[PDB]
Every structure is written in C-alpha cells, then in structure tokens.
Image (tube, coloured by chain):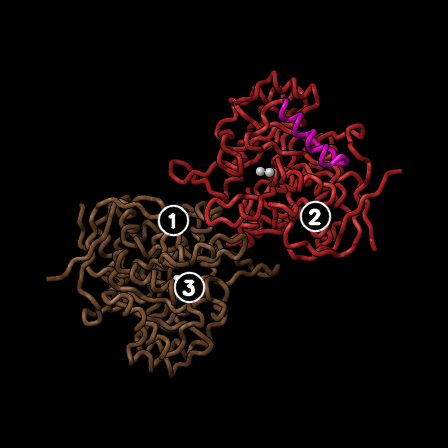
Chain colours: A brown, B red
Amino acid sequence: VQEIDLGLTCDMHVHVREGAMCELVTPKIRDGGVSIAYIMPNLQPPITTLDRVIEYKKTLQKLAPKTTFLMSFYLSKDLTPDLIHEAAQQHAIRGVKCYPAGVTTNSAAGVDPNDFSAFYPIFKAMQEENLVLNLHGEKPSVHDGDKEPIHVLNAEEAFLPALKKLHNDFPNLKIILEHCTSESAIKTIEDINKNVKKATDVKVAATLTAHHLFLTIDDWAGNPVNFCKPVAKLPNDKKALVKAAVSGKPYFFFGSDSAPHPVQNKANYEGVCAGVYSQSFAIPYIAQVFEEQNALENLKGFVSDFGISFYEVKDSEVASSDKAILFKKEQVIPQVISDGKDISIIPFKAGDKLSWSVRWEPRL
Amino acid sequence: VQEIDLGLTCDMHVHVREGAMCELVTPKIRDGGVSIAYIMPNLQPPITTLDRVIEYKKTLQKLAPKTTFLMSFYLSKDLTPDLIHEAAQQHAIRGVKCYPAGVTTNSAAGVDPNDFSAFYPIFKAMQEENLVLNLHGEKPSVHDGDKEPIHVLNAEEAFLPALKKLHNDFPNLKIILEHCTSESAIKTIEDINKNVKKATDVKVAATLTAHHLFLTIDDWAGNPVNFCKPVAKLPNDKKALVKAAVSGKPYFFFGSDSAPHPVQNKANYEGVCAGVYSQSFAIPYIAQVFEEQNALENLKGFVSDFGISFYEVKDSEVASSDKAILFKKEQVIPQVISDGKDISIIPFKAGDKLSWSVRWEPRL
Ligand SMILES: [Zn+2]
Ligand SMILES: [Zn+2]
Ligand SMILES: [Zn+2]
Ligand SMILES: [Zn+2]
C-alpha cells in the first residue's frame, strides 16, 4: 500500500548522548517514526548509578514528552547486585547493556568477555528482576601469534559461544544479541529458538539495524560515515540479515543503533568514531527494505509487535498513544543534520531520497 | 653498528604524482634507500601519450638526478600497437599498467577485467617489444546476481582467472600481479612458476608492498591512513605474504605502492583516498620485516636482485652507481612528511621506531 498503520513503533537500541547533541537528537526519535526507545548507557562516565539514570530520563522526557523511554545500566565494575534490585523495583531501568572493553564508542570501562564470571552475581540479580541483558556481542581483537586471531570480521562469530554459555547458565534471563551482522549469528539465534513458536517463549533475541540491511564492507572501506561496530560484513551476511528482518519471526526486531557523532569526529585520518546516525529517518529506512523484499505486511511485526512483546511493554508505560502512520510521500535526506550552533551530523544515506514519510495519529 | 650492502635497490611500484607533491616525494626515493623506481601512470589524465611520458620522466630526473626511472603507460583504449612500438623503440617506457575501472585512485577510466580481449593488439605489441604488463589485479565489485558477489576482500582472488588466461594467451609476455595481498594469489603465483629454475625463466611475478607485510583489516578499520587498495586482509593472508617476501623465490620482489595523498585527502568522512605513503623509509620498513623473520640474508634478493633480473635493468641505464647500505642505527618515523608549504603527508607507521637506517656508498 500507501499508508500503513504501524501503531506504537519500537526502536530497541538508541544513542542520544548528552548536552547539545542530546537536545538535537532526542526529538528526532519521534520525527523518525519511533514511539518507544531503549536508551543505551555508554555516556562519559557510563550510567552506573540510580540517580544518574533517573535524572537522564528526566532530561529526555523534557526534551521529548511524547516519547516512551526505557533505560539501562552500563555493565560495570562499579555495579553491585544490590543496586540491580533497587533500580528494578523503582522501575528506573529495563536492562543492563554489556560492552566488551575497547570494541566500540565509550567501551573503555567495559568487560572482558572471556571471563564473565565476576558478573554472575549481577546476572543472577538481573534474572530475578526480569531485566534484559543486552550484549554488544564482539570479542576484543587478538593478533598474538599462538591462538586464533580475532579481528573486526570474525569478532562477532567468536562471541557466539559466550552468548550460548550465558544463555545456558541463566535460562530464564531475557538476553539480546544487539545489532547482529553475520550469517553465523543469525544461525545461532535461529537455533536457540528451535522450538519456540509464537513470541512469548523467546528468551534470546537479536536486534537488527537499518544500516546493516543496506551496507557491506565495500560501503565503509573508504567511507567513514558508514563505519560502525560491528562492521558491515559480506554480501552473504547482509543477505542473511535482510532475510531475517522480513522473516516475520518473533526473535528478530528493530534496534537502530543510531549513534550520533559530530562530523569532525568522522573526518579523521585515524581513530574515526564508530557509528551510523539513523534516528531522523529510522522507520522510512526500514520501510524501503520491506518494500524491496515484497514484505510490507511483516513491517509492523518487525518495528512494533516483537519489540513490545519481548520487552513486555504495557500500555500503562507509554508516554503517548499516538500511532505511527507510514505514508508514501517522497523526501530527500539532507546532507547534514544541524542544531545551527556547533553540531553537524551526516545522516545515514545522506542525500538519498526515500519513498516513505511518517506522521503521527492519535488513537480515538 | 652492523651494515648490509644492498647494492642497487629497486622499488618496482612507485607513485610520485605531479606538481608540488611530486617535488616533495621524488627525492624521497633516494632517501628511503631506493636506487631504481618503476613509475606508475595513473595521473589525472593518465599517461597515454609519448610526449607526456617523455616530459614526466625528465621532470623526475630533474628532481632526483641520482635515481633511475623506469616509466609506464596507463592501459587505455587510446593506446595503439603503433604507439607501443614507437614508445618502446625510443626507450620511453618499460611497461604498461592495467587498472580495472573504479577499483582505486584514478582507475576509471580504466578497463573491464571481464574482457581484456579488446587490448590484445596492445599486448601483442608489448610482447614483441619486451614490455612488462603490470596488473592491479582486482575484479570490480559486484553484489547482485547471478554470480558469486565480488567485494574488497575477495576481489583479488576473483581476478586470478583473468591472470591465468592472460598468461595462457601470451606465454612470452612478462606479467606482474602488483601488490599481492592474499594467500590465494601467492599460491597462484608459485603454481604458475612451478617449473622455473633460474631467475631468468620467470615470466609472471608479483610485487609485495611494505605495508601489506605489517597490516591486517584491523589496522585500517577506523584508520583511513592505513586504507589502501587492494585492502589489507586477514592474518592468514599477512602470514603468507611475509613468507613469500622472505622466500628467496625470484618471482616475488619489492614494490612499495607508496601512494602519497595530502592529509586532508585522508581525513574525509566520505571518499577517503586509498593509499599508504612509504617512500621516505621504504627499505628500512622491509628490513624490519626481514629481521623479525630472521631472514636478512634474503633481503638483497627481494629489494634488489630479483627486480633487476625481471625488468632486465642494465648498468648502462643506471643513473647512479651508489650502493644502498643498511646500518643498524635506530630511528623514529616522524609524525608528518611536509614540504613546509601546503602539503603534509602522514607516513606509514608514523611515530614508530625502526631498527635500520640507510646510507649511500660509492662503488669500487
Ligand atoms: Zn554496540
Ligand atoms: Zn549501540
Ligand atoms: Zn594498485
Ligand atoms: Zn599503485
């Protein structure tokens, strides 16, 4: 069609930073077609305390009163089981996000995924509170010269056993392999979900971004704006990801990993910041894929039903009941997204035109 | 300190550009320890005419009177067998370089390597004139069907059947697979040379760069300064390249593919120029590798003997008979190479220490 009622859309992987960047980006969650956002915690310093996560949400709600914000802790050395219980009962967090140390933006305070044991008391506490464990599933790189090298291309596959071990050791814990990028990872998620049918059985899920449904290594090799973690991989991988996205299966749903960086932090000869900014046109990006796959009927599941179901989002939490209406009027993605002061963002697929727009409708 | 007499060193794959950039880099051939340079032709517009290649070489000779320059044409529809014969008879070129269109800097308007048939009159003339056919051996990327998709990691392997067919159809043509980056290509080169005894029988050879002896995908994921074509690939590829370089086989020799770009052309958020600048310390970079492999006794063959033998460089051509002497004095690579005007280049391994330096000694 033209005009599709997507209802209460979900983006379960959002970065909105702080300060002026946050003031620019947080209103764009709504503008991009997203009602519900799961907010990642890799701030400087990481979000590891109750007061910080409460005030952060306050800041976000003031900037965007109609957006529903689900918050998270950064899996940290500082964290204790005791704070996990406290934060959960105050409904101050919906999950804890794990960054392996050094693999991505603001991950230097993260963990070694070879030895998760020191966080098992944290994971047991999360398991009891029905909290979500989000994993940036990549092992840190190892060249070494004795055991198998780990690099940006196999670091996701090399993480898959750690995922299984965590799932085995905490079988009631809801776990997400965030932003999956490889056929290997799809197969592992498919397998873990062998005989779960109809949604409520899913304990381990994976989010898929907009940009990994378009990008391959060829697109970021010479183009830092398309460089993100985990890196876009081979055509065979993008094929597995697109097939999963339009599949209608409840263990794949949308998480943009929209990651804003000022343009000066992309135009570096070294230390290019990882991340693709997709917030401003999130749902229109995804619609393009589903149109091309002749599967617009599975769109509402991928960007709404499955994320709501897995995170158990209740209508009583929702900051606005407005529905996201996808309507097929052309727009051109600007070359830059700016606050008119010092922040310029290069948006994903800058300069390209999209077939779809999104507007907001009240429920009556 | 310890000293190694390398004789008349050869760098059979050099980019020196034009204008002020050329004035900066051309004297660095000498400074990096290289006596003989094979000059690539991908200028804007490419070198496809006799008068242009005559003038260019004179310009280089003016900038560096002690450096021996071997020149090339860019493989183009513009070329004719009559121009090949004329250019060779005037000793104006030693070879012709083929760029597949779109695969690297100033490579479109290059050729299609699902073809090469349209250039067979050129290859016949080259074969008759004892000219070398240099190949940037990567197939242009293809993601859509039918065929197995082509991307930056398999594009070299995907080129190897074009190499075999050319060698089959022109068994007396000297062909070089420039800057090999994959284990597959190394093996293909060895297999092609299965029945070769004595260096002079080699018809198909490969050059190896300095930087592909150090780099893997992780070194350029996020660091445009290490981004070049063909892209540095996996640890297994790096190991195979290092083994070939120290192998003592006459069909592998040094070609830096030193590719200078002003730093602002590397610090781009899109369209990063491909290329690593190694001219300023060319031979010391290689020495570091040969030392680490305990193969210094093979250094001279790789950077001198085998290139001279393959290109048949005669003492009567050599612009200076000074010998390159390696001496084991430690040095630090500067942060930038600059002309003190408008050009700064970030050199390969900027800031690192090298065990060896280079000096020049007169013969007799
Ligand atoms: Zn991540
Ligand atoms: Zn993220
Ligand atoms: Zn090349
Ligand atoms: Zn080159």
Q: Residue at x 60, y 61 (%)?
A: A144
Disc 1 residue type (three-letter):
Lys
Identify the residue under disc 3. A136
Mark 3 or 2, closer to the camera: 2
Which comes sooner in the sequence, label 3 or label 1?
3
Quadrant of the image for the N terminus of chain B? bottom right
Q: Is residue A47 above or below residue B120?
A: below
Q: Label 2: chain?
A: B
In the picture, measured across the screen, residue A104 lies left or right of residue B40, that is left
- Amino acid type at circle 2 is Phe
* Chain holding disc 3: A
Most distant residue in the left direction: A364
Magenta highlight: main SS: helix
**Type of amino acid at the residue the image marks with label 3:** His
* Secondary structure under the numbered disc 3 in the rendered image: loop
Magenta-tinted stretch:
B51-70
User: Where does the image place residue B35, in percent across and percent down from the top left?
Assistant: 75, 38
Is residue B61 found inside the magenta-colored segment of the image?
yes
- From the top left corner, tell me how far across and down residue A223 is, in percent: 46, 48
Q: CA distance from mark 3 to mark 1?
A: 18 Å
Q: Residue B281 shows which numbered tag?
A: 2
User: Which corner quadrant of the figure contains ligand 1?
Assistant: bottom left
Q: Is mark 3 within 8 Å of ligand 1?
A: yes
**Residue topped by disc 1:** A238
Label 1 sits on a secondary structure element that is helix
Judging from the image, mark 1 belongs to the subunit labelled A
Residue B272 position (above or below residue A131): above
